[PDB]
Structures are given as C-alpha cells and as structure tokens.
Length: 218
Length: 211
Image (spheres, each protein chain N blue to C red):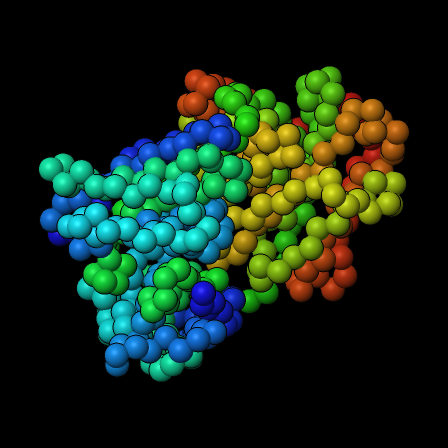
C-alpha cells in the first residue's frame, strides 16, 4: 500500500497570486519513465474533474496556468495567475500501485480582510419545549477568517459533548463564512438552569463575545 | 463528448445491498467513493473487454463490478452495507487516468427510516439588524429545501448543512438577517420542504413578547 499527504491543507490566496500545492508520497510513484500521479479539482457538490495527468500533463480544457512538476516521492501543482474559477479543493491521486489512493485534499480559498462575526443566540421555541427537548441555537454571521470557536456555557459551566456545528461555504459575494451551532438539552435539564450563553472566540474579536439569555425572563 | 450517467440516490438499511448503474455515451471503468466532506477512496476497476476485475482489499467480497456490454452500462454492487458506507459513489472511465467521472450516486445507509421534520422558529430578541430563522429538526433522509417568502427574500439567507444527530435523524438551521426597521412592516415565512415524506410547511417568524 501507498499513502499520499498534501500540504498545506488550507491555502488563502487572491486573484492573480501564484500558488503551489505539494503532494508527498510514501513510495516512489515513477515506473517505466512514467510519473503515476494525477491532480483533481473539486468544487462543493460536484464530481471531481481531472486537472493534470502523469504529474505534468494538462487534462482536456485545462488552461495553461495550471502546471505540475516532480519526480519520485514529491510532486507539486502550481497555479500561476489565480482566477476566480480556481478557488476549489484539489486532490492528488497515485496511479502506480493498486489501491489507487488519493491524498487528503487542499482547499484553496479566498483571502480577505478580517471580519468579526455577528453573534445571535436563540432560545428554544415554546412549541418544541412541550415536545420535551430544548435546542438552543447560536449563530455566527458573515465572518472571516474561517477559524472560530463556539463555547456553550450553562450557568457558566462550559458544555462538552452536547453541541453540533455546521459552517456555510465561503460566500461568493463577500468571501465570509457563517456558522450555526446547536445546544441540545432535555426539557427537564433546561428547566434547572437560569443562564444560557454562547461565547465566541475569533481573530476579529479583541476578546470573546458572549450572547446569552435567562430562561423565564424570555 | 464522453459522458457517464449514474443511477439516482439510494437509501438502504444496514445488512442490505445496493447496485449502482453507470451508463456510458461516446477502457477501464473505476469505482471511487467519497464520504461527505471527506477525501476520496478507490473501490475497484473492471476492464469491460475481458471482465478482468481488481478490488481494494477493504472491499474484498462485498463489491461486485459488472458490465452489460449491449447496454453500455457498468454496475457496482455492494453487499452487507454498514453505517461507514454512506457516501457519494462515482464510476470513472480510466484513460488509464481517471479522466471521465460520473455525476455520482448518494448512498445512505442507516437503521433509521423516513421521518418528516419539525420546524421551530428562531425568533429575534431585542438594534438595527435582526436575525431570525427556522430550525428544521428530526427528519430523515436528506435533503430538505428551505426558502424564505417563496423566494422573494434571498439576500442575507444562510441555510446550513444538516447535522446527523446521535438519534440518527438530521437537523439544520436556516437563518436570515434583515433590518430591525422592517419587522413591523414585513412578514418572514420560511418554506420548508421534505420530499421523502411529502412534508411541506410554512412557518412565520416574528420576535417574541412578554419580555
């Protein structure tokens, strides 16, 4: 078996930058003068499309600003003038030894100025509570960069293992992300505590922002 | 121009099996899979002209790769399906390079069964921007669509990717930001659809009172 690893995993560039992704292999990928490595481009919710084959050859309709170099155990993909259409996730795939494995992927995303999130907390609807479950929802709106931490605190006890998050794709107009987090308690446990708090740490924020409500004062 | 049209999405209970069709128009046929948000994983290949097949060790004796030559169709059969097998599945023509991909076929493998969502409002609080939305909760399987005011309000909407709960049902939020100055002159209804249960719901969303 043979294992590829890409670097970096995330890369932030602007239109016109020259950008280089690296695929490293656990074995040599050359045989018979053939470099046995392939590059793919994938966009959210689409099948992959081949960019490069035999390390350095352009696939059909792949513009010339995409190129690849390398030999043996280390390979690179270079995009010379980033075009808007190029922000993508890129995979390397080895074709010498059979599992045909892929690497983990490298996401190329749009660089922009730091933007602090807008934070909103939502208490559970009356309707839901009578069913017996409380979902508390915390919203981080239109922030960049992507890295963000949400901490749930109930009566200033930080929660673990009862929240789930999901994040939106980078916004095509303003190049920010948004994040929704959900804190799930039983009706019974929700009724024992007064303070429900959503604390958000982000590079845009001099210090964490808390949004909270007090149950029964809502 | 080379095209590979795969069969539609499948929802299968554990221990059951699934057969994905791949129809060619216009070499090797590879099968690859990707779990949502994950990297890709090669299952196997078949050379239609001798029926010669090779498989990834992971899928010894669950995978069956076949072709119907007279209908230009490849098939991928995967037995004894388990949770870990939920993935988009693609057939690929190998050049020898995997140069032509199908659109992919979502296979969902879960002990769970069809359930419509409960839609609960996310009501705003109070400051000049207002955040409101809908919690579309405890439904199965994906997807649900979500719109606002019948698609009139599209600006500022974020519909989030569902999360799979420990219960094994899905739940997602859809939120929108609007001027505070509008919540007394303009109504906000989220329109939530789930086809797999024929669930259509419209839920109006307004800030709450009693302070």
